[PDB]
Image (cartoon, coloured by chain):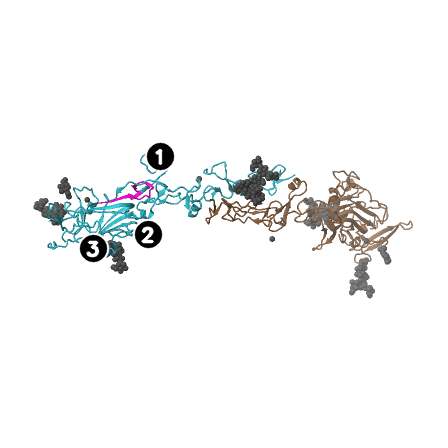
Chain colours: A cyan, B brown
Amino acid sequence: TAQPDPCYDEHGLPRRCIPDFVNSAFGKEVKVSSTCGKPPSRYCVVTEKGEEQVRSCHLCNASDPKRAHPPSFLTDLNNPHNLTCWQSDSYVQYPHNVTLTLSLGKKFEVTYVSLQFCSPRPESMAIYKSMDYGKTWVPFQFYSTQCRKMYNKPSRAAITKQNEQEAICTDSHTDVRPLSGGLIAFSTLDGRPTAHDFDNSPVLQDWVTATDIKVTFSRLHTFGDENEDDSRDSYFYAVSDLQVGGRCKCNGHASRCVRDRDDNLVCDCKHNTAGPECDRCKPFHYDRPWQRATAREANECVACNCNLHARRCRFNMELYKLSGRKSGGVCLNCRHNTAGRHCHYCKEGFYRDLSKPISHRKACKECDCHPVGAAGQTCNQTTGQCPCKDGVTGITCNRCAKGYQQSRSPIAPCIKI
Amino acid sequence: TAQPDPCYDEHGLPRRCIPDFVNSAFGKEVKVSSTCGKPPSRYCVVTEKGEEQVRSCHLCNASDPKRAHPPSFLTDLNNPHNLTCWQSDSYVQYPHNVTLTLSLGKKFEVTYVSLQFCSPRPESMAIYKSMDYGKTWVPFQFYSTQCRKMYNKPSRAAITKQNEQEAICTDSHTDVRPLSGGLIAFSTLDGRPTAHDFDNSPVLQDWVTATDIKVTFSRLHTFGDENEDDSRDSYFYAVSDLQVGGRCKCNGHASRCVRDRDDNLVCDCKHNTAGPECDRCKPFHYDRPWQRATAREANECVACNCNLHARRCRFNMELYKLSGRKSGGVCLNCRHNTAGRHCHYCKEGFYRDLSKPISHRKACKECDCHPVGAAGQTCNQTTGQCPCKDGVTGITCNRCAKGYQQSRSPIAPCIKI
Ligand SMILES: *[C@@H]1O[C@H](CO[C@@H]2O[C@@H](C)[C@@H](O)[C@@H](O)[C@@H]2O)[C@@H](O[C@@H]2O[C@H](CO)[C@@H](O[C@@H]3O[C@H](CO[C@H]4O[C@H](CO)[C@@H](O)[C@H](O)[C@@H]4O)[C@@H](O)[C@H](O[C@H]4O[C@H](CO)[C@@H](O)[C@H](O)[C@@H]4O)[C@@H]3O)[C@H](O)[C@H]2NC(C)=O)[C@H](O)[C@H]1NC(C)=O
Ligand SMILES: *[C@@H]1O[C@H](CO[C@@H]2O[C@@H](C)[C@@H](O)[C@@H](O)[C@@H]2O)[C@@H](O[C@@H]2O[C@H](CO)[C@@H](O[C@@H]3O[C@H](CO[C@H]4O[C@H](CO)[C@@H](O)[C@H](O)[C@@H]4O)[C@@H](O)[C@H](O[C@H]4O[C@H](CO)[C@@H](O)[C@H](O)[C@@H]4O)[C@@H]3O)[C@H](O)[C@H]2NC(C)=O)[C@H](O)[C@H]1NC(C)=O
Ligand SMILES: *[C@@H]1O[C@H](CO)[C@@H](O[C@@H]2O[C@H](CO)[C@@H](O[C@@H]3O[C@H](CO[C@H]4O[C@H](CO)[C@@H](O)[C@H](O)[C@@H]4O)[C@@H](O)[C@H](O[C@H]4O[C@H](CO)[C@@H](O)[C@H](O)[C@@H]4O)[C@@H]3O)[C@H](O)[C@H]2NC(C)=O)[C@H](O)[C@H]1NC(C)=O
Ligand SMILES: *[C@@H]1O[C@H](CO)[C@@H](O[C@@H]2O[C@H](CO)[C@@H](O[C@@H]3O[C@H](CO[C@H]4O[C@H](CO)[C@@H](O)[C@H](O)[C@@H]4O)[C@@H](O)[C@H](O[C@H]4O[C@H](CO)[C@@H](O)[C@H](O)[C@@H]4O)[C@@H]3O)[C@H](O)[C@H]2NC(C)=O)[C@H](O)[C@H]1NC(C)=O
Ligand SMILES: *[C@@H]1O[C@H](CO)[C@@H](O[C@@H]2O[C@H](CO)[C@@H](O[C@@H]3O[C@H](CO[C@H]4O[C@H](CO)[C@@H](O)[C@H](O)[C@@H]4O)[C@@H](O)[C@H](O[C@H]4O[C@H](CO)[C@@H](O)[C@H](O)[C@@H]4O)[C@@H]3O)[C@H](O)[C@H]2NC(C)=O)[C@H](O)[C@H]1NC(C)=O
Ligand SMILES: *[C@@H]1O[C@H](CO)[C@@H](O[C@@H]2O[C@H](CO)[C@@H](O[C@@H]3O[C@H](CO[C@H]4O[C@H](CO)[C@@H](O)[C@H](O)[C@@H]4O)[C@@H](O)[C@H](O[C@H]4O[C@H](CO)[C@@H](O)[C@H](O)[C@@H]4O)[C@@H]3O)[C@H](O)[C@H]2NC(C)=O)[C@H](O)[C@H]1NC(C)=O
Ligand SMILES: *[C@@H]1O[C@H](CO)[C@@H](O)[C@H](O)[C@H]1NC(C)=O
Ligand SMILES: *[C@@H]1O[C@H](CO)[C@@H](O)[C@H](O)[C@H]1NC(C)=O
Ligand SMILES: [Ca+2]
Ligand SMILES: [Ca+2]
Ligand SMILES: [Cl-]
Ligand SMILES: [Cl-]
């Protein structure tokens, strides 16, 4: 680890390591259902400086970068004295939802998502995630005043061990005031019966995993007095930069996340692991199956030992369990005359040449029998002794014994006296 | 030997035996160069009853069975009070030879050939034999008055050990008187430097061997006084039955000689021997090579032991000598999974099933390996132990050991704890 490498310890040998925690939103462009712009639109702010509840109406023009509120302002530079704010059309209302989506383009373990509003917080909204890259969409958290009516939800009920992957519906962070600067923040891991036990809880690891994330504002609040109608008065969504705090899901096997040949984000997978999330593991590491890392056991994939005599290999769960969870990895395409599980013994008509280690290419000489002197071409595949005929000693059977005279006739090449 | 069998002794086991000694001429038709017949011919006899040297001339007519002298009379019923006589034309003279031939149609060891004449004996003649059935002809004995002139022969010279197969030329049995009843008789084995040692002398065994036999009368005697010319006076050949005493050559391996499927004479070969003369030996008796019989060692051919697992086999002279003259006979087409010289051990991918004797058909079980449990299909071919993989005991490798747990995965079917 002669630079930063947290993945390998000071022995040299591997442990567990995580990519750095980030705002995965900054610089990354957000898709929206409703920007005011075309047409240029009325909007009003009711502002209580002093104690005076004053109405100030303005011009929402996406053609003018001084009056424009594009989705760019959701992931620009945050600076709360100088709030840059995306803004929607007015009184898009229940049933009609404004949605926003952010695609990460990579599985992230989500810690939180925060939305800072320069408008009132929604009366009713919901957050959604995608496990796949935007195909199915999965509920995450609901924020309705009337859960039973709106989302067919119990209001602030139980999370059990059976359904820890459960969105609660909660009349909270759904207050009208603050009229400006209100926070939505959802944290994934609150309220789970293994909240503590995240390294060791797979159901929670899946919960927080997501590729794309989607916010849905489903209703607004109307203040409910006689004003004089103003049209669509001041009822719109607007947010002054967003954050999605998360870590790049590499299952504890990778150092940092990097841009690809294909200009996609992937894990720089370290521990003989493979794929985008390091969620399978590398070819010819199929001795011992895939598992997520922890500090306890780094749990990583390890090479099939085929002795330099094979390149393709596969796992066997059966052999893994009957090896006592040590090894299930068996070799195919056995080269250099080798055979059996680990390409470990010489195939028939070769015997093991012990003068040479197994990793040596000629680890296995041919039986090399004298065809006349041998009663068989296949030798015993470890002793290398070809079976000789009546008194034809020698490994290759290339020689008469003492007491046996040589002939030239090949059916009877040695004979007694 | 529940009938005559001299070939097998009272143990049951074989010794040496010979066919009976015969006149091989009787009943068998003789080929000739000169019969008087057509035309009917003059012939005279000069006969000294009392003391009177009287000339009696007669009529030689093959159309009249009372005056006919056909070659039939060379091998008819002998009865010297009643002489039946074949007769030639008169004064066929040097250079002109009358020849006779007798084909036996079977190799015979000749003892003697006797010709009894009712005429004077030839001044000059010769006997010939055929080793092959009448192709080459080989000289045998010469009977000239002037050997040097007639046959380019020394008169009564030496027989050496280098040329025991040598016809002598001998002015003997070449006397004019007897004018009637004279004998030619040639005995083969006279005068040989291993005359005694016939069972043990191969060069003499070849000498006396013959298939066809040929007599050649090359000159006559003329009495040389002034008579009154008589024409062709009385100068002809005539013989009153012939004999060829011999034994049917079966090289001491056969009981008697018998007529074939093809109506040819052959040896009834007994001692696992084969051919006409028993002069090779039978298929699948090529352990230990062919040899003639004697009383000393019957020397006979003996079966290749291929253990009921082969039918074709061959000899090896090299293996015979290095077996110490015991066995040179090796097996081909090894059935029932057997292998090696005598089809004696199990071929690769079978091992020897000792529960069963070698002559049993299933003397050799398949390795019969458990294909999953074995690291090899070929077992050690006597132990029958297929090479099992990591802790898969058993001969067929059909079982995990104690301390090894069974899997269903075929690359790792047993595993420790
Ligand atoms: C939050 O607001 C979102 C916007 O909607 C507004 O507010 C709501 C309350 C209503 O008053 C509505 O009228 C307003 O406009 C709202 O999202 C919308 O939700 C509806 C219902 O879930 C979606 O409708 C369905 O659309 C699909 C097709 O559209 C999709 O695919 C096409 C491509 O083919 C895409 O281009 C679209 O973008 C979509 O992705 C229909 O197939 C489906 O039909 C169903 O209903 C009909 C009868 O109407 C039946 O006969 C059928 O069998 C089906 O059952 C729906 O019509 C709508 O797509 C979605 N719009 C947008 C723009 O995302 C969200 O639901 C609001 N939340 C709540 C809780 O109200
Ligand atoms: C015992 O008498 C036998 C009969 O002969 C009579 O007496 C002799 C002395 C002469 O006076 C003769 O003229 C009398 O008729 C005698 O047998 C004969 O021997 C001769 C010489 O060895 C044989 O001659 C050779 O014949 C072959 C071909 O004939 C053979 O094959 C045919 C088939 O193609 C058959 O049908 C025949 O039956 C034969 O089997 C010739 O190729 C060969 O030619 C050679 O000589 C010429 C010149 O003349 C050369 O140019 C060549 O290059 C050759 O060298 C011979 O002519 C004859 O076949 C044979 N006849 C019979 C009926 O068997 C025997 O030799 C007398 N014994 C002694 C010691 O005199
Ligand atoms: C919403 O946001 C938009 C900003 O994008 C505001 O638009 C401005 O509106 C004023 C209205 O008076 C525009 O001013 C007038 O434009 C007339 C036409 O000018 C056009 O073409 C010239 C070039 O040929 C451009 O430079 C100009 O931008 C326009 O596109 C002029 O006839 C007027 O002239 C008078 O004032 C000028 C001041 O420079 C004097 O020089 C002249 O002599 C004369 O007295 C006048 O300029 C202004 O152009 C718009 N600005 C921009 C940045 O687009 C909307 O007004 C705003 N509010 C609402 C309620 O919608
Ligand atoms: C090449 O091929 C040959 C044969 O084809 C193999 O050799 C045979 O090897 C086995 C085991 O290697 C020999 O014997 C058997 O050993 C069993 C285990 O004990 C051994 O190992 C333990 C430690 O693990 C030692 O403490 C112990 O001393 C042994 O060395 C025994 O359980 C067996 O005994 C049983 O059978 C015998 C008869 O065989 C009975 O009499 C007993 O009562 C008991 O029931 C057994 O002794 C075996 O004998 C070898 N063969 C021959 C012919 O002698 C090579 O090992 C093989 N190698 C390869 C890799 O291919
Ligand atoms: C050599 O050997 C042959 C033997 O094969 C002798 O041949 C005999 O020769 C005599 C000569 O006189 C033959 O006899 C005469 O044959 C004449 C013709 O007959 C032929 O046809 C009849 C049937 O039609 C046959 O049966 C017969 O065999 C002949 O083929 C006759 O005209 C003669 O007839 C006279 O005698 C007979 C005897 O029976 C009387 O009945 C008649 O009336 C008449 O008087 C006479 O028969 C004789 O046939 C031959 N015999 C045989 C067995 O063939 C040679 O003679 C002998 N010698 C010499 C020197 O060559
Ligand atoms: C199946 O396959 C296995 C192995 O593939 C064979 O088993 C091996 O068999 C050999 C011989 O059968 C074992 O050992 C060697 O034996 C030599 C001969 O001695 C044996 O036989 C004589 C009688 O003929 C006995 O008196 C004697 O006690 C032995 O039983 C020794 O000369 C060898 O010793 C030499 O090598 C050793 C090291 O191996 C040295 O330390 C010595 O100094 C010396 O130089 C040797 O001991 C051999 O060990 C077996 N294998 C294993 C792994 O143990 C089966 O026989 C075979 N069968 C068939 C038919 O296929
Ligand atoms: C930001 O600061 C400037 C002075 O530098 C001030 O004129 C401006 O009105 C401020 N903007 C907001 C939106 O508070
Ligand atoms: C044979 O015997 C008979 C009498 O039975 C006699 O007439 C005949 O002449 C004899 N033949 C010879 C050739 O001696
Ligand atoms: Ca901002
Ligand atoms: Ca006669
Ligand atoms: Cl290589
Ligand atoms: Cl069979």
- Say if residue A212 shows up in the picture: yes
Residue most toward the right? B50
Q: Position of residue A402 (x, y in %)?
A: 62, 36
Badge 2 sits on which subunit? A
Residue under label 1: A10
Q: Split into 4 quadrants, where in the image is the C terminus of chain A? A: top right
Where in the figure is residue A189, as x and y percent of width and height?
28, 47
Closer to the chain start, of discs 1 and 3, is: 1
Q: Which residue is mark 3?
A: A96
User: Is disc 2 surrounded by few (<14), some (14 to 19) or many (20+) residues within 10 Å?
Assistant: few
Q: Earlier in the sequence, mark 1 or mark 2?
A: 1
**Residue interval drawn in magenta:** A242-266
Say yes or no: labels 1 and 2 on the same chain: yes
Amino acid found under the numbered disc labelled 2? Gln
The quarter of the displayed image where residue B147 is located: top right
State the SS at label 3.
loop
Secondary structure mostly seen in magenta is: strand
Q: Are marks 1 and 3 on the same chain?
A: yes
Residue B269's mark?
A: none
Check residue A264 for magenta coloring: yes
The amino acid type of the residue labelled 1 equals Glu
Crowding at mark 1 (Cα within 10 Å: few <14, some 14-19, many 20+): few
Q: How many numbered circles are shown?
A: 3
Residue A390, x across and y down, in percent: 61, 41
Disc 3 within 8 angstroms of ligand 1 (CB): yes
Q: Position of residue A83 (x, y in %)?
A: 17, 43
Q: Where residue A162 is drawn, which disc sits there?
A: 2
